[PDB]
Image (cartoon, rainbow, N blue to C red):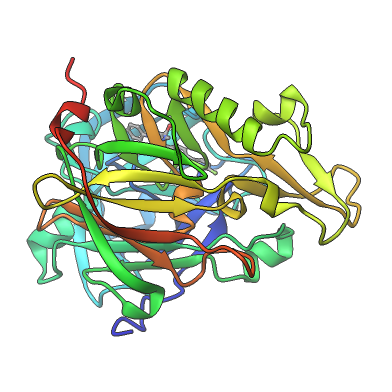
Length: 390
Ligand SMILES: CN1C(=N)N[C@@]2(c3ccc(-c4ccc(F)c(C#N)c4)s3)CN(c3ccccc3)C[C@H]2C1=O
């Protein structure tokens, strides 16, 4: 592990998001910021809000610069509106550098800040193409790389606890690591396997095969990436295109058929509980996603366990049972490899080489009989045909 200053710098959980501490302004104002590989704006609360105990106060920063322009982001998971500007930004448990970056000061919002959560802003780590209002607003990481000698790469280790963390626990527990500018070998086991970044906007990738307990879902691979497949730390679930979700759930139900679960469980709405320690992990199947490799006609697979796709939740009766929600859900905007997927792996966003690497995470939850895996290579033909074009 060569990046000790950044190891264990994240806090949070899949249902709340994972955040890192950052400072903005002069003198520095500390804020907790959600790490989001699914967007490209650095946006922070900049006005009082019932669910925030602190916010960016531009009038107290001597280095604040007003861009005299607004920004409006429509409902996705809450909507917000703000004013653009720039200021000096740093990451305390990060690279020892300070950079001038764009900041969207959020002044009005709806269903964006969450009651009970501990983050006050979001750090969009994707590319300029999807930045708002348009691609002229340079994202934070681009600024960081342009202004310093930090390598054009970051890596994320999101650590699910495997059980519920209460209010106090989630604040005191280490939720993972965001290594800025490098790869820390203490965070994974085995080898790193890389898949190409198909296009630089979201972190888009191409899935070429899907298995449920080794059984091929057998769909035209284009369906797996309709209309795109992305890696998104800002999404809790593994989200799959409608048709794929339908086929996958049928197969997961069949594999776990020795126990019947209500429709509400498969819809991700209701929890299921078992007596303490008796969760029947073994009846649930492993899920493997094969990704295009860097070599022609070669692919590799990442395999997750039910310990990744069943999200631990507190029982309504705060009993002693072990309860969970099914964290695979449908999407009309493509596959989203969210926290569910990311908690099983150390993920390397190698922007410099336009590729994303995966290795088994040193903090993934498993049991004595099965473990998450990253394996290859496999011979796979016509993988380009798996990508979707509008
Ligand atoms: C899926 N997703 C996302 N990855 N980022 C955004 C998020 C807003 C709130 C998020 C949130 C809140 C609580 C949580 F627990 C988790 C998790 N996990 C995530 S993610 C920012 N965004 C966006 C930003 C700027 C311009 C355009 C779009 C599009 C939003 C969105 O729908």
